[PDB]
Length: 209
Ligand SMILES: [Cl-]
Ligand SMILES: [Mg+2]
Image (cartoon, rainbow, N blue to C red; front, side, top):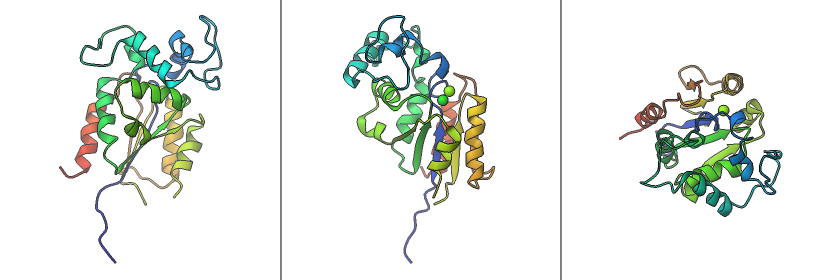
């Protein structure tokens, strides 16, 4: 009847810990640093990482700053425990896709939204950018991906996860919704081995320059 946009539609389903960061989730949430972000923290005592209330976002930011320094031009990319942050290549990737609005970003995680938002906030993302993330955190990755895809067909669907079994869960969800091999780009890589800069150029290539 009228004009219709020819822009491609791209959906990303990505793990967080060990995919966007360089450390696996099991190696993140029981560390002293993660546990220090939970209300009632006592050193060398472990609290339920998922359901304990987190310290407020202002104090979380203060704890990141004391651990890593200010995230600026003086930042030490070689300091200890830098692998708990997003790599620079992953930060550049998310700055770009968190403004292409024909790209939808879904983080599918056993971690929790308050923590991931704190990591993004600490590494320089704005409140508007973080609000374009959808964080699916039930821990049941087939169910979360399947639910997100119910009901506008995507041109390309990205699936990224360092865990073989959670990757397979997400892929089964996407194939269950009728996406074929030409539309799927799945990446099962060990922590630190994802090619974020190449995925950024692959994404940019789908769109006009
Ligand atoms: Cl996970
Ligand atoms: Mg992971």
